[PDB]
Image 1 (spheres, helix red, strand yellow):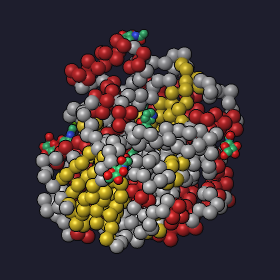
Image 2: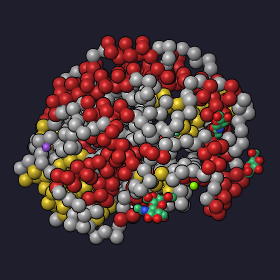
Image 3: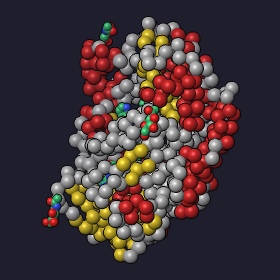
Image 4: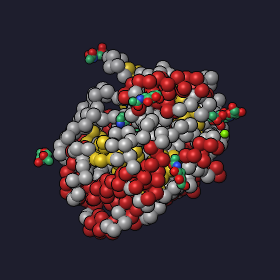
Length: 585
Ligand SMILES: Cc1cc2c(cc1C)N(C[C@H](O)[C@H](O)[C@H](O)COP(=O)(O)OP(=O)(O)OC[C@H]1O[C@@H](n3cnc4c(N)ncnc43)[C@H](O)[C@@H]1O)c1[nH]c(=O)[nH]c(=O)c1N2
Ligand SMILES: *[C@@H]1O[C@H](CO)[C@@H](O[C@@H]2O[C@H](CO)[C@@H](O)[C@H](O)[C@H]2NC(C)=O)[C@H](O)[C@H]1NC(C)=O
Ligand SMILES: C[C@H](NC(=O)CCC(=O)c1cccs1)c1cccnc1
Ligand SMILES: *[C@@H]1O[C@H](CO)[C@@H](O)[C@H](O)[C@H]1NC(C)=O
Ligand SMILES: *[C@@H]1O[C@H](CO)[C@@H](O)[C@H](O)[C@H]1NC(C)=O
Ligand SMILES: *[C@@H]1O[C@H](CO)[C@@H](O)[C@H](O)[C@H]1NC(C)=O
Ligand SMILES: *[C@@H]1O[C@H](CO)[C@@H](O)[C@H](O)[C@H]1NC(C)=O
Ligand SMILES: [Mg+2]
Ligand code: NA
């Protein structure tokens, strides 16, 4: 018997478990699918980055109707610390209107204003050295970055010289320096804040900052290498869970909570727990002979990710050193590793293949001459066309409300819809941050070891291709600007300067886009039940008591940026909500 059981030991699960166990009268069990990492160089050292160590095995998509029916390997964490243990350590808040929009969907107490103190509470920013800030153009607003919270973040202590050419090129094509991308807008270029502890130049993942930090606590229990297979009920009250070994041994165990069950199993895990437990669409549950506890057609609907594109380049005059010097120059690689091992300086403080700066842009910044044409197309098309016919009408209503919020974001000069990056080597990256497409994640069986059916439905909403084509063209502007032309870049096949029309460009993008940056969200959405929502504004699952969703399954839609910073802050916020209801310390 525990006070709380948390299903999943990732960013949201560990943050919540940490905060709840600050009260010695409160016991928590975190049940986590994956093992404890072993402090491998691939995890702790940015330059050694090896995310594949703890990928969840045997997840593959359905054929992707929007991407030439390609099937893709699905990437999500299976490890204590979840995504934080194996992600690229990119630490960015969303824009103000992301959180304001979540509130306006019918979620009282959700706004930029209510989130800011939880962003601050979550973290400790360590400033870079003054010479690197000056040379690098590293800026921040100390007033809105935390100084006392457990997540350490800072910057690498080095930049590849080519990052200078790219910064100036970006400035030449209307991506100006951003004072602080953590201040609720990020229109232009800025240094990437990195979830690194500057004392050791090592990863500050949730395993460290929300478990190891507090693991002397006898009330903070962890069970790695087990799966929560089902929620247990007395009537509509969630009272416990069944768990099994992740390795598939024919064993099942029941464990009980006096106060609540929290789901923290992520975008691809939480909906499976709900559906196996009879919380989900009665059509699916009836087909599988699962007794319905709560008929919620939103469970496993509204899947979102942030598609990526990798654009290959050749250079006649690239500057040495660059990120690819680490792979192609054994001498450079040895000297940089020796340097890191001695004085913790140099290229090994940067996540392997990344550079130090990045660019985010609104729709009107990407497409200043045409953004109103894209908005008109999106406005003209019924929200229902983005979903299969027969989609539950509550789910269509919630999608329409999300869509109307995103079209306002499209009109907003201060909300990002795309990211541009150049690692300093043979490729650039373009990320689509705000897809209008929605996918699904549904169980195929009652067997808790069976992968769910994962259908991203990337590029099914035709507006996504118009936005993404505009983002591609802006990246092309950066590479053609005078500061980059000195390095002699040219797009390589299957891209190329000879692809000049939207149709020629998008035909190649349809074959190369990745549905996912492992940013899966929004499959147990926080919206009103009559809008196809799964959880209330307090993250309580509709139709049952003592059951909440903490992981980014609860998000209505994707941010202007990567999810990690908000996964921490959203868990900080929920810890206080739970403490308030249950009168905890
Ligand atoms: C390789 C890679 C790279 C990136 C990213 C992810 C990944 C995998 N992301 C995304 C980001 O890390 C991710 O969105 C967050 O970790 C989500 O936090 P959650 O708490 O929702 O899930 P998270 O995935 O952290 O945790 C869920 C946990 O539940 C466990 N689990 C699932 N089913 C279970 C069950 N039935 N029982 C028990 N446990 C169960 C899983 O094992 C996992 O540890 C990212 N973001 C960003 O901002 N910056 C970045 O650089 C990156 N890069
Ligand atoms: C990571 O952030 C934590 C939390 O603010 C920092 O921990 C503090 O460290 C100082 C100096 O070691 C101590 O005097 C404080 O008592 C610590 N506070 C807590 C709550 O732990 C740590 O310094 C940060 N890392 C870096 C590089 O600054
Ligand atoms: C899925 C995973 N994604 C990341 O590492 C995030 C990467 C990320 O945010 C950024 C990279 C550059 C600027 S920002 C992954 C793993 C392996 C290969 N490809 C992708
Ligand atoms: C994808 O497969 C479907 C069959 O389900 C087919 O109708 C369609 O033409 C295919 N698309 C492409 C681009 O081949
Ligand atoms: C920093 O910005 C200045 C312009 O203010 C520019 O001259 C310089 O090249 C930039 N350096 C880097 C590394 O971005
Ligand atoms: C698991 O054990 C139970 C009880 O012995 C048994 O009924 C069932 O056949 C077993 N399942 C498998 C796959 O071994
Ligand atoms: C390889 O890296 C070393 C170490 O910095 C450098 O001296 C050398 O010029 C590099 N070789 C090439 C071919 O770039
Ligand atoms: Mg200093
Ligand atoms: Na409820």
